[PDB]
């Protein structure tokens, strides 16, 4: 009634938490519960919306305003609109982030601690989680004007390396190399928007590059000493130049504003590790300008 | 018997014995018991690339501090067969056999991370998929780097475009010393064949 | 019906909805997992039901 | 047959061959080496197409 | 690529036209110029015998790791094409008559895709 | 509801990495990924050729030039063609390598460090990975000549031990024991090539030996003090001797060249360990003749 | 259909092409493994498809 | 040909001789024999009473 | 068909010849194990054959 | 997608080489080979007597 | 205070230790956790049978 073992000696390896970093598997964590099948029901009548609010389609399809330009009645034709905001009428086509501010505070009387702060759209905030991206970028260029402001506006796409001025701490564009003389838009894909009645235009720039995916580094740590990962993150830039100068009467304002919304479609991402040097850290704004921020280390 | 060179190649086979594909199959039922067809299957067997890889405590070390030294040698199969080819594709596997005179009064662990290729240790974060083993109970640290690339294939010694595919980063709390043995994963292959380089024989250091 | 040399691969999967998984189309949540208040969550199924294991036997 | 190379073959006395402008008498047909089974390169055909030369000239200019 | 060869019938010789991809990119020991005779001729090539084939043709594929070849901002010398002598030129010893080989080279493109419009061109 | 264990005590062995040196199995390495089924697709549209470029058939079927001989108009009949290259008109039939050069540099003023360098064909380079081989060897003997060089040429196969001159550091053949007097080719398998119009001949020598497999050691470490593994690697040698002396006019060259290509068919190999004393090491050529090379050890 | 006293031997295998495996015949690569862009790689099959495990449920 | 592990981390307890005092089970004692199925026949013609 | 209270006993067995196993009758060797050069040794069966695992896939 | 363990705690004994002295079983020795099914054919045409 | 390991390699028969490499199929065990080193040498022969 008590027979012998017929089963083989099984080979073994003592690995606690084999493959804990994978999204799919069978997890060995003991529940602090009553039932081993402790399982909540579906999401019916929990959140106020029954839309899957965590799909990469739904999150990246949330538009956000990246530029509010100012197109005066004095600005020249065939010259990119550079008034007010940084980056002017040069919008780098891409899912990562391209604009950053720099906060400078004092440690001593002879030293300043700089800190890069980045304004993120809800598609730029998701690409920072990953290493590489590939998406169809969408833009909606909207002109804030009256019924009496008339003009024409050109939005052309130019692929590849962006004409930039690397500063000692940041990267700005170069409007000197994007005038009508040196940079003709006769061969680019362009849209010539009329502003007599029409206001908006939606532009869907697909993914065009010689790479299967582009980096998601972007403006992170980009300066004169280091600007390679900036150029390899976008593959293109939209440029907004006037064809016809802004025609406006004297009884209206001498300005219009060009508001550019940004989102993304057909989004795929590659690697669940950020390509940045430091961790993904949310900038918590300090109470006073003199005070400091949190500095996350990298030593283990 | 006209004048002029010609063509019409005369394939001759000596020794009209028996079709060779029968003789080969009859010779491996008696001398091997196995039939190695493809060289791709030799990229899935782990061969040791070093025997004493000495490291220091609390130092994030990329594998490209070791692999860049041993790609030139051609010792294992991934560095000997790479001289016949010009491209590759797919992830790589690693095993880290422990050979450290460990102490009991510490708790040694072995982390492993991802860097893109050819970055240093300070210009990358540690927020990614990781793996940890304890050499007091599990002396072999087995890890697999996938193929996370911007390109569908990778050349050898490319341009200043760096960090276009992922690699491994090593970490340990103690100064360890290991035996590294790499192989390709289930998708690893070479391609785009060229001709072989030379080989190297003995080194006697003769008396004159 | 999936090509893999490992015998049964991992974590046997359920079914979902009919759409593309990204590329905005307002994916409904109730369609993704199929466990409403019914005989499909195993703890409500054990008392609807009334198996012997809910009584300690 | 051999791989990754070509040899002297002494083929037929033909191949007046035309590369759309240029011909190319070639007393005997030249021996060809090529990719043995072509699967060529990147996805430049999936980005756009193409253009031609009378379709370049139909672009508006300032 | 098409070579055109033309020598008189009293001159013999043999040449080899191999191409080495990334030859000026790789480590020096991985080049074609730093290997043996049996290693040079192990590359993809073709014989050019002076008295059997006066012309050889060769298709060199899309030899780039990335997608479509970048024309703007960069010279991208991907594949090198070499012409090696296997045997020396076997002419008669009568000088002042010029035993001679006189090779000519023709090249063109094929399987062409030319896609994205820009306004720039490289210097 | 919480019943007892009915399962037996399973026997166990603590072996991490059981059988890591086998090509087939189930590997215990944790992926640093997102998905446990992380799997690239097939090789469609990756490499420029859709031929399996790693099959032993395809790699060893790549021909390479092992000999470029020189057959003068002065050379005698029934004597092997030994002008220019080493090994003359004696080609050892076999997949391993038989020719090596020796590089001599100085350590001190009283010592020289020698180093053996071996020219490998793409079949000789693969057999060095393994211990034993068995293959049908193919050869293509091509004469570089004009339309006015006429002669006849003999290529006979002689199985077994090769007539060699062991030097103190290398092995060369012995042309004194392969003349027409001492070594008649009346009983060998031979081909008598005519050179009035015809140029090439392809010879397929099958595997003939009293052994099921031959060693792949070859010329590695072969000298006067050690030459057993050289003889047990080939089982035969082709010998190229003139039947008729090279007949040529004065208006053509007094030389022809015999170019011998080498590849292999029906290749089987045995053991995935090299039979050599040292590791397989690729010779990286130094920059200057005075400089040294890498010396790989064997201690663990 | 293979003679072996071990019950099921190892690593359950897929199928390939019709040729001899060595002895030069230009073996095609696309025929060797049978996983094109289709319902045969298990990660593209889980979203074509749309099982519940790609949504975290 | 050498795929990855899809099997879970199995929980474990190191109990030699689990339940040795029970009359029924599967016993882990190694036989000092030739055959793993070393088994005498029935008690026919052994003892003088059946 | 063998009386044993262990569920499946050990090492699943093949078949042989028709004779008594001792008591001299010149037992043939080729009849004992049934693996000639055919689709019955699993490594020659994988390349006859030509499964995907002999190519590394 | 990453559910919990439902499998029991399995009892265990750490015996390397359980029953190595028996002629029949499943042996835990790692082959120093290429193929895990490394297996010679039958004895046809090996010894001079069948 | 040491970490003992047991490697095992292949030589052909009757060579010494210095006239063979260590680049082959191997096996490593750790006697602190696995005191039995189990290894199998296959039949990689030039001949179909071996005399004495």
Image (cartoon, coloured by chain):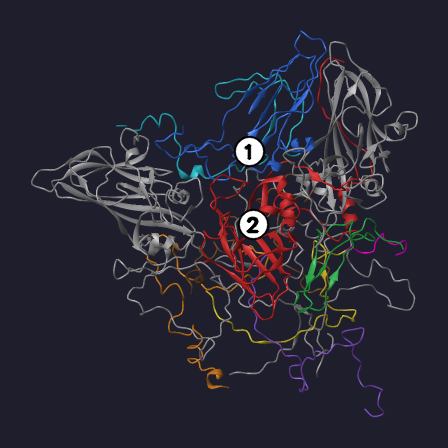
Chain colours: B red, C orange, D cyan, E blue, G brown, H purple, J yellow, K green
In the rendered image, residue B167, in percent from the top left (x then y), is placed at 52, 51
When asked about the image quadrant of residue E117, the answer is top left
When asked about the image quadrant of residue E3, the answer is top right
In the rendered image, residue H15, in percent from the top left (x then y), is placed at 63, 79
Q: Are marks 2 and 1 in contact (CB under 8 Å)?
A: no
Residue neighbourhood size for the residue with mark 1, other residues' Cα within 10 Å, grouped as few (<14), some (14–19), many (≥20): some
- Front-most of B65 and E63? B65
Q: Circle 1 is placed at which residue position? A: E24
- Disc 2: host chain: B
Q: Main secondary structure of the magenta part?
A: loop
Give the magenta range.
J40-50
- Front-most of K26 and D14? K26
In the rendered image, residue C27, in percent from the top left (x then y), is placed at 35, 59
**Whether residue H50 is situated above or below residue B112 in the rendered picture:** below
**Whether residue H32 is situated above or below residue K13 in the rendered picture:** below
> Does dot 2 land on a helix, a strand or a loop?
helix
Q: Quadrant of the N terminus of chain D?
A: top right
Labels 2 and 1 in the same subunit: no
Q: Circle 2 is placed at which residue position? A: B65
Q: Quadrant of the C terminus of chain D?
A: top left
Q: Is residue B117 left or right of residue B183?
A: left
């Amino acid at each position: 009634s008590k027979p012998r073992n017929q089963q083989q000696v099984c080979p073994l390896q003592n690995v606690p938490a084999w493959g804990y970093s994978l999204y799919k598997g069978i997890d060995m964590s003991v529940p602090l519960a009553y039932d081993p099948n402790n399982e909540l029901g579906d999401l019916k009548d929990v959140f106020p919306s029954a839309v899957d609010e965590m799909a990469i389609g739904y999150v990246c399809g949330n538009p956000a305003v990246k530029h509010v330009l100012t197109w005066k009645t004095t600005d020249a034709i065939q010259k990119p609109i550079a008034n007010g905001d940084d980056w002017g009428g040069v919008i780098p086509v891409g899912m990562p982030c391209y604009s950053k501010s720099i906060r400078t505070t004092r440690i001593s009387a002879t030293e300043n601690r700089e800190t890069e702060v980045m304004d993120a759209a809800p598609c730029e905030y998701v690409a920072n989680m990953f290493s590489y991206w590939r998406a169809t970028m969408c833009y909606r260029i909207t002109v804030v004007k009256t019924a009496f402001h008339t003009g024409r506006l050109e939005i052309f796409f130019e692929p590849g390396v962006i004409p930039v001025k690397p500063t000692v701490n940041n990267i700005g564009p170069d409007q000197d190399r994007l005038t009508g003389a040196v940079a003709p838009s006769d061969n680019n894909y362009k849209y010539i928007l009329d502003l007599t009645n029409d206001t908006e235009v939606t532009i869907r720039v697909p993914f065009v590059s010689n790479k299967m995916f582009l980096k998601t580094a972007g403006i992170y740590g980009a300066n004169s000493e280091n600007n390679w990962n900036f150029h390899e993150s976008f593959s293109g830039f939209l440029c907004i130049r006037p064809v016809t100068k802004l025609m406006a009467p004297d009884t209206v304002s001498d300005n219009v504003s060009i508001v550019v919304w940004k989102w993304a479609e057909d989004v795929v991402v590659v690697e669940p590790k950020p390509l940045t040097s430091g961790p993904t850290q949310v900038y918590r704004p300090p109470p006073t300008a003199s005070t400091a921020v949190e500095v996350l280390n990298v030593e283990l | 018997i006209n004048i002029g060179n010609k063509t019409n190649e005369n394939v001759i086979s000596f020794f009209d014995s028996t079709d060779a594909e029968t003789q080969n199959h009859n010779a491996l039922m008696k001398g091997c018991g196995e039939f190695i067809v493809n060289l791709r299957t030799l990229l899935r067997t782990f061969r040791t690339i070093t025997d004493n890889w000495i490291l220091q405590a609390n130092t994030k070390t990329p594998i490209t501090d070791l692999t860049n030294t041993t790609d030139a040698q051609g010792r294992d199969y991934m560095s000997y067969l790479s001289y016949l080819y010009r491209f590759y594709r797919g992830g790589r596997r690693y095993k880290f056999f422990n050979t450290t005179p460990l102490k009991q009064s510490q708790t040694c662990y072995i982390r492993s991370f991802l860097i893109p290729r050819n970055y240093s240790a300070d210009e990358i974060n540690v927020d990614g998929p990781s793996h940890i083993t304890y050499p007091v109970i599990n002396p072999v640290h087995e890890v697999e780097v996938p193929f996370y690339s911007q390109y569908r294939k990778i050349p050898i010694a490319s341009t200043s475009d760096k960090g276009y595919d992922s690699s491994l980063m090593y970490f340990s709390n103690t100064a360890t010393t290991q035996i590294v043995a790499r192989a390709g994963n289930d998708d690893f292959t070479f391609g785009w064949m060229i001709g072989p380089p030379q080989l190297q024989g003995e080194s006697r250091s003769v008396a004159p | 019906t999936s090509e893999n040399p490992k015998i049964g691969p991992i974590s046997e999967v359920a079914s979902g909805v009919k759409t593309t998984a990204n590329g905005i189309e307002r994916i409904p949540v109730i369609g993704e997992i199929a466990k409403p208040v019914t005989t499909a969550v195993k703890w409500f199924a054990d008392v609807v039901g009334t198996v012997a294991a809910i009584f300690g036997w | 047959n051999v791989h990754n190379t070509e040899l002297a073959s002494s083929t037929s006395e033909n191949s007046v061959e035309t590369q759309e402008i240029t011909t190319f008498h070639d007393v005997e047909t030249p021996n060809r080496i090529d990719t043995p089974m072509a699967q060529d390169t990147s996805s430049a055909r999936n980005m756009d197409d193409t253009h031609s030369i009378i379709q370049f000239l139909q672009r508006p200019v300032l | 690529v098409k070579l055109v060869l033309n020598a008189n019938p009293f001159v013999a010789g043999r040449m080899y036209l191999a191409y080495s991809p990334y030859d000026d990119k790789v480590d020096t020991a991985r080049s074609v110029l730093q290997t043996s005779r049996a290693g040079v001729t192990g590359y993809p090539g073709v014989e050019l015998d002076f008295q059997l084939d006066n012309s050889v043709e060769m298709t060199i594929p899309y030899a780039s790791f990335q997608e479509a070849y970048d024309l703007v901002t960069g010279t991208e010398d991907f594949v090198q094409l070499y012409l090696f002598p296997i045997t020396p030129v076997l002419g008669p010893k009568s000088e002042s008559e010029s035993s001679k080989v006189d090779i000519s080279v023709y090249m063109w493109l094929s399987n062409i895709s030319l896609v994205i419009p820009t306004y720039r061109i490289n210097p």
